[PDB]
Image (cartoon, coloured by chain):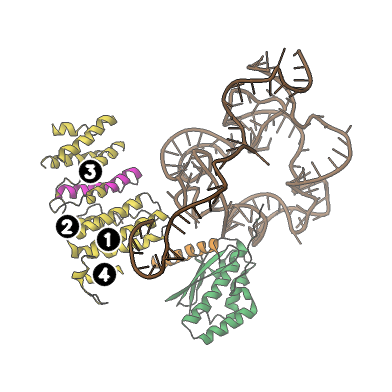
Chain colours: A orange, B yellow, C green, D brown
Amino acid sequence: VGPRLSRRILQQARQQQEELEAERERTTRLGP
Amino acid sequence: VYHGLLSFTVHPKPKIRKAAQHGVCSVLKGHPAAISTAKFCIQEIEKSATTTLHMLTLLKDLLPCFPEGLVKSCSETLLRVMTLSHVLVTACAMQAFHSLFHARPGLSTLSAELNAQIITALYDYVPSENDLQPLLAWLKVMEKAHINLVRLQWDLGLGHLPRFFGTAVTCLLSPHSQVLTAATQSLKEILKECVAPHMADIGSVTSSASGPAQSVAKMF
Amino acid sequence: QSVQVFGRKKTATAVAHCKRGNGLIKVNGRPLEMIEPRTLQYKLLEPVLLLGKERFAGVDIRVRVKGGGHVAQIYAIRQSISKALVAYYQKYVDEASKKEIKDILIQYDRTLLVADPRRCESKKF
RNA sequence: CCACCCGAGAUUGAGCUAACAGGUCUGUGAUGCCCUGUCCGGGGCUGCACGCGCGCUACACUGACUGGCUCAGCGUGUCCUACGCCGGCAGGCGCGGGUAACCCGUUGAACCCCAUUCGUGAUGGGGAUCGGGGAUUGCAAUUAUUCCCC
């Protein structure tokens, strides 16, 4: 395929996987 | 007189601040005065943007000479300004935790159970993926915090390892080269120092380990 | 379990994700019949009409496209939909079904499985 | 590179330093030829009958106007810009990000696609040439710097 097209394919194929796995306030205190 | 020396640290003139910054370090490292000066440090952060940079520089090399309760209070206070998205205060506070762990404090200064609360708290930042300025410093302290936690209690040390190696493998995908070099340099120094001498006490591990050997299953 | 493929045109790159389902096809979150150039609607529906509505009933495909243009994306969408099914029928259905899909899908139009190796030519001094 | 086994021999003697088509630095020939400017203001730098060449916009219905929908890549920069408020537009005021696969930027590009009006009419095609006003950069806009409205 080549360097430029494959870079966009791999980046796009990764981002479709993440929105399958996807389907608060930070802990300011450390001792409960 | 100690409070007279200390109250000039917030001074706007840099020369007056620079000597007072160096003066406080030499007095404490050379302690009953440690408790009061930390109480000054916490209240000054709560009062306030430019002065906080000088105070985090004060807290940079003054965390190691603190007792447990004040480290626990400081660990909150350094973590409060993390909620602010300002970058220079974030980097100094990130580097402040570095000087805490790089000194490798004793059991009276830093307890073993305190470090577990710190590392579990720091997991909530992971800045985005690819900014390279704090992310090198972020995984520098997670190296330094874990290597210190292992030295105190080793079998708990393997307990917290798999989650860090979850992000460390994941953060290899950042497009910056210096992320890649710093990441594996962190990971190799954990393995050469926290796992290699303590491997013999673990013994042989199967696929159905239960104790700390199960951590080694999660490493690989 | 699922299968993750790609199909391409000049710059319009597609990725397709196919798994068990009831037969819904989505592109960028939109159905296959709402993709904007409605003149070339049949190019999107060729791998569905050639194979039949029954053959796609055991699979749900979700396609993402980025780059290229309006008709370059349609040629990449129809490639990765058909290429996702021939990969899914290979790994989880017997090869006899995969051979007969790959047979009738090449004799119609060779660009549904093998890509077009045409790209813009550069200029030199 | 150093030490060593075997091996006659893991190096002993005869010849070669040299140079400046880059030049420089002011030393010499009563050396060969041949002669005895600085600052400041204003103007125009293609003003246009014509000959010869690039280009842009068009002559419309495979089209123009109005609305809606929907897709790039090479690059870019401390000058690219995000966001909020004001004006109808050019344009103002404030506050942030980015020395940069980090912000601009999921680079929301134009033809294209779908609806509306127009109906062969130098016409809602075409926009020159003009009149009046507004805004911006500049020491300065006159012979229209540039942009916007009628």
Q: Are marks 1 and 3 on the same chain?
A: yes
Q: Which residues are magenta?
A: B68-95
Residue C71 occupies which quadrant of the picture? bottom right
Q: Is residue B87 magenta?
A: yes
Q: Is residue D143 left or right of residue B78?
A: right
How many numbered circles does the render carry? 4
Q: Give the residue type at disc 3.
A: Asp
Binning the other alpha carbons within 10 Å of mark 3 as few (below 14), some (14 to 19) or many (20 upward) gives some
Q: Which residue is mark 4?
A: B216
Q: CA distance from mark 4 to mark 2?
A: 21 Å
Q: Are marks 4 and 1 in contact (CB under 8 Å)?
A: no
Going 62% across and 69% down the picture, which residue do you hit? C116
Amino acid type, residue under disc 4 in the picture = Val
Whole-number angstrom distance, CA of label 1 to CA of label 3:
24 Å
Q: Is residue D108 left or right of residue B53?
A: right
Question: Residue at coordinates 65% horizontally, 67% vertically from top-left?
Answer: C39
The earlier-in-sequence mark between 1 and 2 is 2
Q: Are marks 3 and 4 on the same chain?
A: yes
Question: On the image, numbered disc 2 is attached to which residue?
Answer: B112
> Would you place residue B70 above or below residue B167 in this image?
above
**Neighbour tally class for label 2: few under 14, some 14-19, many 20 plus, Cα within 10 Å:** some
Looking at the image, the residue that sits furthest to the left is B32
Residue type, numbered disc 2 = Ala
- The answer to whether residue C54 is left or right of residue B132 is right
Discs 2/3, front: 3
Indicate yes or no whether the magenta region holds residue B93.
yes
Task: Name the secondary structure under disc 4.
Answer: helix
Q: State the residue position of label 3.
A: B61
D46 lies above or below B68: above
Q: Are marks 4 and 2 in contact (CB under 8 Å)?
A: no
Percent x, y for residue C122? 64, 57
Q: Is residue B209 above or below residue D55?
A: below
